Image (cartoon, rainbow over all chains, first blue to last red):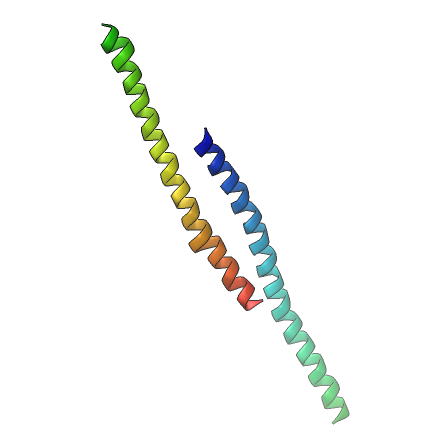
Length: 50
Length: 50
């Protein structure tokens, strides 16, 4: 019973760290998109100035 | 009769419970594999990228 409770607790830990990793991957993709958009927008603005 | 049906039968149930204990320990080791070398390793690489 103790080992089953340990497995269950470690499964909630798996789920929590998996939500954390899903948030991290969403934030990584969002950071990549924000880079490409923002750097292209700054390029457009600097090109208008140029 | 007492041994075969009560004492040795209880010992057989105890051996089955010990086998279940070993299976739970193996499942726990697999969860640390998926967790430490996995979801924590995935967390580390995701945090590095982020």
